[PDB]
Each structure stands twice: as structure tokens, then as C-alpha cells.
Amino acid sequence: LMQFTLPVRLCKEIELFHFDIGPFENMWPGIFVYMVHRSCGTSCFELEKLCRFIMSVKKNYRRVPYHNWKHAVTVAHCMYAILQNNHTLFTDLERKGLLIACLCHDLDHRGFSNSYLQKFDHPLAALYSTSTMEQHHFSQTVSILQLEGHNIFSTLSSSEYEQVLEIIRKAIIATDLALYFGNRKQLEEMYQTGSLNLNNQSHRDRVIGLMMTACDLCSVTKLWPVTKLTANDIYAEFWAEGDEMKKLGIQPIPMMDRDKKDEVPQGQLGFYNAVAIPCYTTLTQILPPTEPLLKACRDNLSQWEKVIRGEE
Ligand SMILES: Cc1ncc(C)n2nc(CCc3nc(N4CCC[C@@H]4C)nn3C)nc12
Ligand SMILES: [Mg+2]
Ligand SMILES: [Zn+2]
View 1 (cartoon, helix red, strand yellow):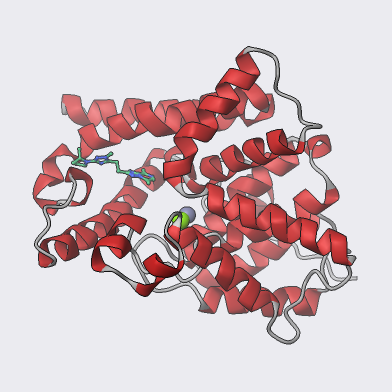
View 2 (cartoon, helix red, strand yellow):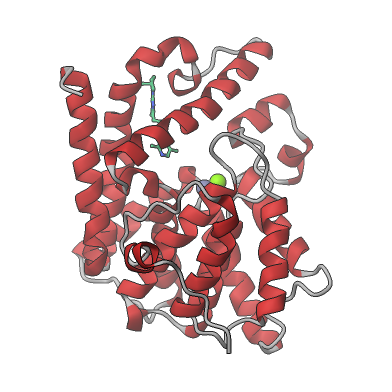
């Protein structure tokens, strides 16, 4: 049968946490299939169905600066690196579901936060009062799964199918960063007091939720030029949202105000200290082989400190 292969530099570097998928969009589908085949097997999905699904997912990501098809595939690769480094901790269904979840987790993102949809009074904010965009992302995933020829899970039983769609629903909802703070605290406390138990389903749910946050934030784990250039795309979205907040007659939060451009280096420090470093610290305690993500995050925090000292 038909293995996907990659050129040698990609074949070796795709295994590393800090891999950058590159600027050649037409190679991203192959990179993803390559990752499914090695983390899941050539038997997991019917190739023709998997390809149809991938191409429909791509079409349902928008041309926005950050929450785009490149972000989706980036987040899936960080998940591939976690899965491949913790071979024996994950079930066959988890292997199947989580790469799909990561590819789907921002489907049909418009470049605006849950908070902007609520203030604008977008219809999605009436349909979904909390985690607004994330319930939408999961809803788009089920839509694409039900297009003809797109059921990549057709070989699973009724109960296995329901289990995988539950793994995907929870992984996608967990990417709402408002939910992350509490999840990480519960995980920290369970780890410290020795109650953490990976046979407990609700414990696994929290661990998978944290892996989702880690994958979603993985721009902070890259080589510094990747980190720094991704930050430009992140603020390009945030600042457009700030502009829209000002059109509604509302002072945006600092993060989203382009007039506070100068404070970016200090905003990045708060972000690394409040979100990123604690995310990868807890992840590393639970899954020791994920330590390269924490080491790379720490390295990028030093680079933001250098930008503030005027050395970078
Ligand atoms: C790298 C990255 N990955 C994912 C996400 C969600 N984020 N979110 C951020 C923004 C962090 C931020 N910046 C600011 N600023 C910027 C200047 C004014 C004010 C101090 N505040 N905060 C809190 N950066 C990331
Ligand atoms: Mg999202
Ligand atoms: Zn995302």
C-alpha cells in the first residue's frame, strides 16, 4: 500500500516539537496524512475519505491572519509530537480523535473572540452562551463528517463512534482559554496530592484538555523567528477586533488596542508567566517526555526579556 514520505529534512524534523510546517500550503495535507499514518496507522482511515475530509476542512477555514488553515495543521503537528513521545499512554480511539480534533478545533473562525461576538450580538452568541466559537467549531466538524464520502469513522461501532465524537467535542471545547486556568489548577492539585489517575475518565479528559491548550499555544515553543513572526499575526487579528470594539463605542482591552503596540514585549511576558509557562510546566509533570515544549517556551520568554532590555 501507499505510504506518504517526506523529503529528508522534513522526515527528521517533523518528529521534533519545534518543527515549523513551512510556507508551502500544498504540502500541509500530505504532512497531516503522514502524521496520521505514523501516530495512528495506515489502517485508521480510508485514504480517499481522509483526503476528502481534509480538503473540506481546509475549505472551511477562512483567510484571517492567525486562526487559519496553517494554525490548524500547526496545532495537529504539536499533538503528533505529544502522541509519538507518549506511545503507550493513549487509547486507539484517542490517537484517531485528537489529530482530527486539532485539525478541526478552529473551523470557520472569523478572527474574533467570544467576547466580541457577545458584544456585537452575533447570532452564534444566542445559540451558544459560553465557549461560543468552540461549540461552533465542533458543530462544523460534525457537519463535515456527515457530508457524503467524508465519514472517516465509518469502520467504528455505534459506541466507538460516539466515544470518538465525545473525545473530539471535549478536546475542542477545552481550546477555550477561559476554561484553561481552572483545568490547569485542578490538574496541578491532583498531581501534587497524588490523586491524579489516568484510569479515571474525567482525569484523562482534563489531561487531554491541557494537551489541547499546549498544542493550541505551541507558537511560543518554536525557534525564535517563528515565535516572533507568529506574534505579528496574533496581534493583527487582536487589533482588527480592537478596531471593531471601537466601532461599537467600546474601549477594547489593552491586548486588542493597536495604540498600545509599544507594550507588546511586556504583554508577551505576562502571557508567558500567566498562561504558557504554567501550561507546559503542568504538562511536563504529567507527561515527562513533553519537556522540550517547556524548555522552548522558557527560551522564548528570555528572547522577549531581551527585547525589553533593548538587546533584540
Ligand atoms: C503568543 C500568544 N499565543 C496565544 C494567545 C491567545 N496569545 N495572546 C497573546 C496576547 C498577550 C497579551 N498582549 C498584551 N498586551 C499587548 C500590549 C498591550 C498589552 C499589555 N496583553 N496580553 C495578555 N499572545 C498570545
Ligand atoms: Mg480557538
Ligand atoms: Zn487555535
